[PDB]
Image (tube, rainbow over all chains, first blue to last red; front, side, top):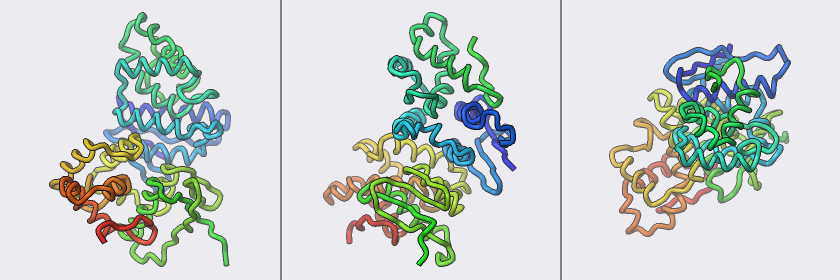
Length: 174
Length: 179
C-alpha cells in the first residue's frame, strides 16, 4: 500500500527518514492506527502510495507532507515563516547538501539567535535538512572543534534526542 | 450556475504564477488528448498563489505545483521519468528557486552553451518542468534585450521562441515576443 525506497549512506534518504521520525514524534504521536511506509533500499529514491509513484527527494517529500497533513508543522506556517523555511532548504539543496567550514560558522552564528534555525517554537523542515547535512562534518571533528561551534553541537544533540526515531539509521554522535 | 470546487488563485505579473499558468498549458497541450473531458481549475487573480480542491487548500508555488501534478497524473511527462531524468529536472528547478528565479549574465552564458546542441534544457524528447521554469524566468530579461544582444544568446533565443509557440496557450497571460 505504502513503500518508500531509499538509498544507503545518502543524505537525501536520511532527510526522508528524519521527516518520518518527525511526523511520528510531533504529528502522529500516540495515535497507533496511523500507517507508516515500509522502507526498502535500492540505488534511487522513490515512493509509492496507492497507485501513485513519486521519484526523488522533493516530489516524495511533498507527497509525504500531504499524506500526513503536516505542512504547517514542517514549514512554521502559524509563525509566518514558510518563505524562510523554503529559502534555507532550497539553498542547501542547491549547495548539494554540503556545508563547508564557513557555512558551519554562519550556522553557528544563526543558532545563537534562536533555538532552531528558522522557528522560535519548534523544529522545522530546515532543522531536519541541516541535521542530516551537518552529521558528516560534525562526526569527523574532535571535541575542541565541536565546542568551537557549540551552538551547532547543542542544537544537533537536541534534534538527536527529540526527533530521531525508528526510521533514522544515523548513529548517535558519541 | 454551480460554484467551482477546483480553484487556482494566481498573481498578475508574478513569475511563479506564470509558471503555474504554463504548467496548465503544458497539461492541455502535451498531457490531455480530449481536453473537454478533463476539468481545469477556475483561475482567480488575487495577491497570493493558492489552490483549492474540495476540502484541501494548498498555498504558494511548490505545494500548489505538486497538487496540480498529482491531480493531472503528469509527473512522468513534466519530470521526464521515461528518460530517467527526474533528478536532473529537480536539480535545475531548485537551483533556480534558490536564486529567486533570477539569472545572472553568467547563468545566461551557461544556459546558452547547454542549448547549443539541445532542443530542451534537460529532456532529449519534449519540454519539461525545467523549460517551463526557465522560460518564465528569462522572459523579462529577454524582452528587455535589444536584438543585437539576443543574437549573442542565439541558442536561448531559439529555445525560447520554440517554447513560446509550442506550449503557450489559453492560461498564459505573458505577451508573446516577436509578434
